[PDB]
Image 1 (cartoon, helix red, strand yellow):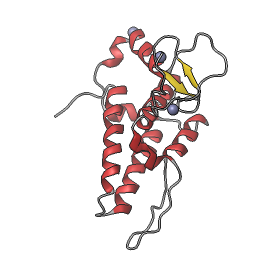
Image 2: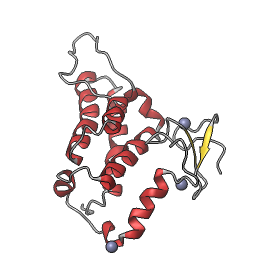
Image 3: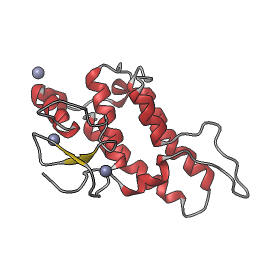
Image 4: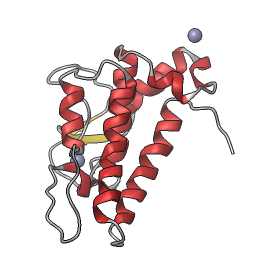
Length: 178
Ligand SMILES: [Zn+2]
Ligand SMILES: [Zn+2]
Ligand SMILES: [Zn+2]
């Protein structure tokens, strides 16, 4: 197994996957690394199994159809994995915890949103469709762009949104377009 957390790239108290060489901090994995379960398989491995059990699940899909899917166990998992892929980027730090807004010439968003809030919402099964999760994720970046206006820091929102969107298209096998 790797000697650093796959998500945050630090050492520490790591739980090792049995079916791949990745390792995780307990609360870096999503869902949080399960208490017992020998062998244990990480979310990467669980996602690869879904694909292997249903090869056709990789054929292209329309985003509108994906969004309307109910959050059954496989879609729950896919959203957990997509959230984890965002946390994998170090620039996720800016969007992880609860923000506050006091900048001359700007007003804060009407509906603040942050990664840890989305993480709790997933854990608490608060989303009934994929659309709920995706809307909250895109709101994070939209709030950031609106608030920061012409400050160059707006780019951090563009950057992490691009990570989100590329991973969304991959995980949910969105049909490729120009
Ligand atoms: Zn970690
Ligand atoms: Zn694994
Ligand atoms: Zn099949």
